[PDB]
Amino acid sequence: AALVVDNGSGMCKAGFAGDDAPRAVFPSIVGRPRHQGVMVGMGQKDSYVGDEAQSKRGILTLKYPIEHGIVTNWDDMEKIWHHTFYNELRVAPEEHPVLLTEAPLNPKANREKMTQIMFETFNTPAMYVAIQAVLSLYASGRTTGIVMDSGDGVTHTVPIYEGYALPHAILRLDLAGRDLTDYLMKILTERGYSFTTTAEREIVRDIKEKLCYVALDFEQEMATAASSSSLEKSYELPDGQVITIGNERFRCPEALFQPSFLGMESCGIHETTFNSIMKCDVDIRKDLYANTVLSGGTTMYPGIADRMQKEITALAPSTMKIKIIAPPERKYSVWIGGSILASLSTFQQMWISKQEYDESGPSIVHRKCF
Amino acid sequence: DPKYADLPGIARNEPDVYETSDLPLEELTSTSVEHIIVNPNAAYDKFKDKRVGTKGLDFSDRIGKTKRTGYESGE
Amino acid sequence: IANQPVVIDNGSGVIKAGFAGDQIPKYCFPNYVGRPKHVRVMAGALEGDIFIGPKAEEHRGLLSIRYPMEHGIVKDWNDMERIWQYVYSKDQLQTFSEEHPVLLTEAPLNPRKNRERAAEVFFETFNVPALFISMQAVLSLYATGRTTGVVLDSGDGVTHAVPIYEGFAMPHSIMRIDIAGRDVSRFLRLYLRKEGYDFHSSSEFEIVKAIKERACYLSINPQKDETLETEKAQYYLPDGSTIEIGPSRFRAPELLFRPDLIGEESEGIHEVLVFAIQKSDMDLRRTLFSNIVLSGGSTLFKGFGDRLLSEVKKLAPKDVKIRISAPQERLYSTWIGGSILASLDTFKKMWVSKKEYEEDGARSIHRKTF
Amino acid sequence: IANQPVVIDNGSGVIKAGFAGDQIPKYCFPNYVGRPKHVRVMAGALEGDIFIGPKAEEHRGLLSIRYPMEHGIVKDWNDMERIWQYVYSKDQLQTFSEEHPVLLTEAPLNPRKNRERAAEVFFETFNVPALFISMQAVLSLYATGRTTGVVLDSGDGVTHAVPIYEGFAMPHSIMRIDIAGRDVSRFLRLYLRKEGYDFHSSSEFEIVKAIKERACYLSINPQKDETLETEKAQYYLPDGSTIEIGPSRFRAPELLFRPDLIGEESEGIHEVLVFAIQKSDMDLRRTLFSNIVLSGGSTLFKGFGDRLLSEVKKLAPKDVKIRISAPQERLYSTWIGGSILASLDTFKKMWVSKKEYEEDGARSIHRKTF
Ligand SMILES: Nc1ncnc2c1ncn2[C@@H]1O[C@H](COP(=O)(O)OP(=O)(O)OP(=O)(O)O)[C@@H](O)[C@H]1O
Ligand SMILES: Nc1ncnc2c1ncn2[C@@H]1O[C@H](COP(=O)(O)OP(=O)(O)O)[C@@H](O)[C@H]1O
Ligand SMILES: Nc1ncnc2c1ncn2[C@@H]1O[C@H](COP(=O)(O)OP(=O)(O)O)[C@@H](O)[C@H]1O
């Protein structure tokens, strides 16, 4: 009996260890109302969380507590974890030990303060923080190979060979789902359809998930988009109003492969995956090309795998065979790994206990992280 | 001044600028290392009359004809 | 054609026209179409069903005001064509549009359909030699005569902050919010009804804009002025009747700096300025804080510069020099910039010729914009 | 030749240029090509798409930085051509390349293709009378005015140790390691992200280099200073914001002494020096240990001399006299050596003439360099 709780910037995936898929999946947001001095009606919650805030988007200002895999407002994150254990999962945190997930190369204060809350506020019996990328490999039953776990908050590239990780080869890029969502708003505003508010940004994320797809040749796709209106698809908003996004459909996910569009002055998700493999030892490169995994929900874009293969193959040597690993459950790839890890009898020892936390302090986490 | 006097919707008796109040080697002094004073004029004089023999010179990774020592002698 | 180019500012509230030779705009009239309020069947009433600028101001109470441009976007194009036709009337300028070339001043990050249709009208309806669409922010710097400078241009329709350093505008650091002078006029009408004076009519909305422009001061501390008993300064209406404004005077334009009070999800005028600087690169931040320029009519509020300086200082880093350099001609700054730009021989290269638009295509106007 | 020969110290971090005989290099500017990343909209902005040296330093925030040479190997030659062109331009020495001979200063044990291309550019693109390529270490000894000494030259790009006894330099005892000042700045950036301050931008990476030079001390005992709670020393960024560096201050420069931290299997700077002496013949070991000369900018770290003297003493034999001598101008020591060598009449014989290069080709340069 143990709890796996993925603390993703976009969506918080929580559930019991051993189960196939996560029990409760809700958007990680806190909804505070745009209140005036006028008195409010009955059935009023001071701050709404998750699926409740997703229902009452109209009035509530949606504030994401985790920004680029860094917890900015801890009071907000506490209210999400309270919604996770007590309401969503229907379980006491004192009974079950809780596994959390942190992105690699995050600030040290993040892991420090995270565990402090779990030990003091919720009074958990044991707490282990893990790297999202390390878990994602277990999903595919692969010990060897690199992963390109692109989330809503961040995208990170962690090469692991024969159950041994290369820490110095790890590269983090701040370009992620929320930056693409923010980019899609700007180009939709250029077409005509203006989306400004926090509630409207959530509707633009629903537009992104459904329509947007990765093009094989961007320049070739822009030529077809100009000539014919075949790529132009219609989407119905919450309001009866319908919109035809056009070429901006495949223009949004292009930003992943060339950040110049967003204006970050950084390497693309294809180029960073190559650079990470080159930073590793020369011998093991072979297996990393052969076992390139794509994880998170930012790798569920239709035809990212085809475009990824093409771009890596061009950069990589001709003799090498480049196979991209795209399992059907990419969105729940971080959690399903956690469920496999927590269930294993070996992992029982690796848990950090309250007694261990009390004596040493919150600094113990940095030793027993990975 | 007379240009802006002509127009109706102009700022009159307002300050133009709103501004804030105007607010007004450790290794090179180490014990371990011995601090030398570089005098190129002195250095130039010491090497002044020193020459090199560029005849039969080959520093390259050429195997032929045993070992070689570049810059044979002066004068 | 060598004949003098005609600058025209597309201000949502007031459009400012004139020749490039003039130091100031000779002809500037309100941007609204005036039709008779009662649907005219009979003779002896207001004839034509069109009253623009000074003719409208004379017979204002009889007519019904309808603004053609909202939030820096043209809603009714038929109305805008009549307005631009009145610019080339016997009343203002008194010239052929076919002879003189034109310069438009569209707000930043507007819809591309707005720019394309604006060009189509000015090339097809009027037989213009050449047209050039430009950004309102870039012009404001030419007027003042400095290359570096952030331009907080608070218009009637839109308030936007564009950072430009050494003649280089960062397009990602641009910030645009819809809460502008027109919204302040709308919110003042609500507070005037809370004082007990209704301005229900579209004509009666114009005198609320006059009340705002005459008497509305921005308090340095809003909470202290609320507790203090007001003088209740009397304003005289067109009919002759007096109205005591009282606390509505100062707590109306406050909604610029704090738009959450009414319940509008926006950043605020102090916030968009700071955010635009913070979004830009770290090296430039100090110089961009050291060079801020106020543009448009919604900066002329009494004690705007005093409040903004205080609200920017607390958000901005400590011990940083913040100079908010307002010109004396803030309302007419955007046009004067265009008048200088138009006069230069470089402008001859920048604009798009009528024959160029026929051959090149639609993109011609967009690609030459920058 | 009557015209003085120009000394150019082609350093990875800073390229130092000047005329032979001069006591100090008159014109020393940072080695990078700055291109504007933001768009030009206004007229009168900064002219050219290439900014090099002091103009690039002033307008750093506007530009995207790109180092042409990495680890003493010219990666992009087009860029290296533009910086050498800028040395001869009006801003720096302001003379024709055809009239003055050149003295280039490359690092030891660099690729042969680098020396070949370096010559090709300096003879074809610039029609120079004569070029001599020399080692950095050999010059550093002429500056101090000593015939016997080992030269530990820790530069920005590469750190190397060359044992030189009574004029002769032992080519098999040369020790070179890629880990250097620029890897310390790269390793500092990684630890600053762990502390929770991000510097993703190429312009922001130059601020990390500024933080390194100002606030980073090498602790005499590494394991001792790790455990003890450190005083969190605040540093002021260009914008004004304060960062607490904390443990990253002293952990960052330790990379030079322990290359295992970044994860490269190479010798430490302390191991490089002793290995270079131990590789030399038995008789000269005592004289080389007595005569140690530190060079390059990366030796200017606070407590470098103290730590190195501690580390060398443990690896070196018992009861041997270890005197580490520092010239006050460590940074400019390499160039001053070049000026003294260039001023001697013996340098005339050492040169490769244009005709000599044109006849034999690449071989002539490889024959006469060390
Ligand atoms: N099918 C899809 N196609 C395209 N984009 C998607 C799709 N599903 C989700 N996304 C986008 O990618 C993000 C994926 O978030 P996800 O559910 O993987 O959680 P997360 O916060 O990224 O967690 P983690 O970092 O642990 O992977 C969403 O926020 C959304 O913006
Ligand atoms: N003297 C003034 N005091 C206060 N508000 C003013 C004043 N003059 C104009 N305004 C406000 O500013 C608006 C004018 O905006 P304007 O500068 O013409 O915008 P644009 O830059 O788009 O042309 C008016 O409609 C009014 O709301
Ligand atoms: N005061 C300082 N403290 C620490 N490191 C420094 C200091 N000054 C310069 N450096 C480092 O030394 C570098 C300069 O290298 P330099 O000696 O000019 O190279 P080269 O010897 O290859 O010509 C800088 O880029 C920086 O990384």
Image (cartoon, coloured by chain):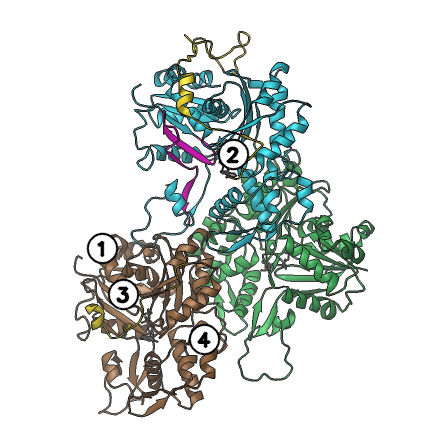
Chain colours: A green, B yellow, C brown, D cyan
How dense is the environment of label 4, judged by Cα within 10 Å: few (below 14), some, or many (20 and up)? few
Residue A316 at least partly seen: yes
Q: In which image quadrant can residue C181 be found?
A: bottom left
Sequence order check, earlier mark of 1 and 3: 3
Alpha carbon separation for disc pair 2 and 1:
48 Å
Which amino acid, by three-letter code, is at mark 1? Leu
Mark 1 belongs to which subunit?
C
Please state the horizontal and vertical placement of residue A197, each as a whole percent of the image: 51, 69
Cβ of mark 2 under 8 Å from ligand 3: the answer is yes
Region of the chain picked out in magenta, as a range:
D10-37
The chain to which mark 3 is attached is C
Instruction: Please determine if labels 3 and 2 lie on a single subunit.
Output: no
- The answer to which image quadrant residue C214 occupies is bottom left
Q: Of circles 4 and 2, which is in front?
A: 4
Q: Name the residue under label 3.
A: C335
Q: Mark 2 points at which residue?
A: D157
Q: Nearer the viewer, mark 3 or mark 2?
A: 2
As rendered, which of A126 and C18 lies closer to the eye? Answer: A126
Q: Establish whether ligand 2 lies closer than 8 Å to the Cβ of label 4.
A: no
Q: How far apart are marks 4 and 2 (CA)?
A: 56 Å
For the residues marked 3 and 2, what is the alpha-carbon distance in whole angstroms?
Answer: 53 Å
**Marks 3 and 4: which is nearer the front?**
4
Q: Quadrant of the N terminus of chain A?
A: bottom right
Callout 2: helix, strand or loop? loop
Residue that carries the numbered disc 1 in the rendered image:
C344
Q: Which of marks 4 and 1 is in front?
A: 4
